Length: 65
Image 1 (tube, one colour):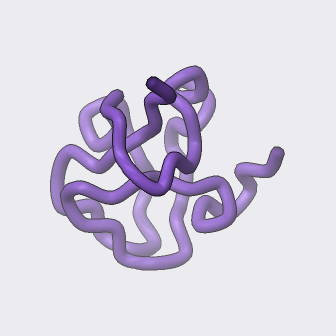
Image 2 (cartoon, rainbow, N blue to C red; image 1 turned 30 degrees about the vertical axis):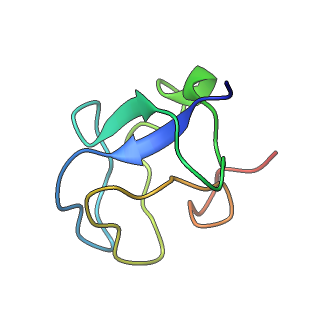
């Protein structure tokens, strides 16, 4: 099964991501894969990202395909 990224804690908007906030877990819809965890570090999202949220590439400003 394809795995994706998911929030681990209450991540506030306009904040930098970390290893704790990011994790591996299969969720739907499958957005960003688990093979980009060390690449999406210190990334600032353009919206509030609470616990249990499939980290997408469009939401992450700067993270492109």
